[PDB]
Image (cartoon, rainbow, N blue to C red; front, side, top):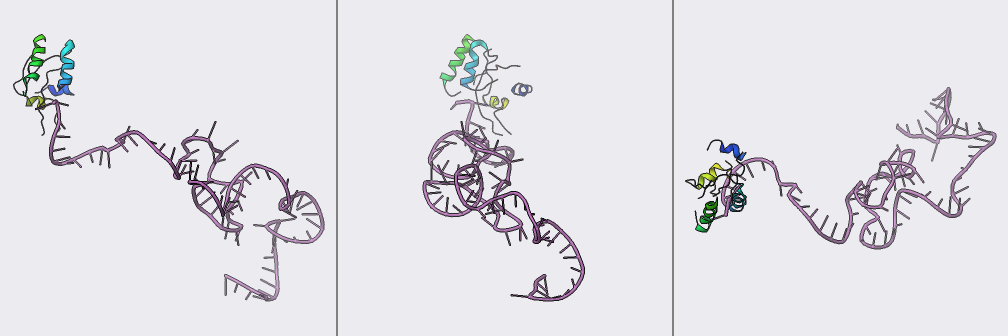
Length: 84
RNA sequence: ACGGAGGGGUACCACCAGACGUGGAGUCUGCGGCUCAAUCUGACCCAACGCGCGCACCUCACCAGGCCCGGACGCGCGGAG
């Protein structure tokens, strides 16, 4: 919302969140969506291991650098690996 | 400007007197022609032809074949499901 832009200068996607949710390299989690099999996978993998849910799916597209400025794109993710 | 017009001068890239040569053979090299898929091109009296500073690959354009975008920057659409 404010300093997050500092961080981006984190990941988005199933293939890259799993690859950082496990092995305990992650940080914080923020769920979303369309299908349970993508809602109760991570959540159950959150059951083992931080686990949180942000109110909206779009602001992730906003907070993250998925825009160019105008065309925000939704994208659920839950891995703040960098967290520098 | 030219003159198989005249008069003055001048030079071993002109001559007198001589000397050393080339054109005769074998060979290095370049130039035309023939050949090939290609035998890459410029220059042709003085004022083109060991000259464009040594070509197995690059040099290298030419022939037979094959990799890559190494398409900046703006606008429109899509994109981390």
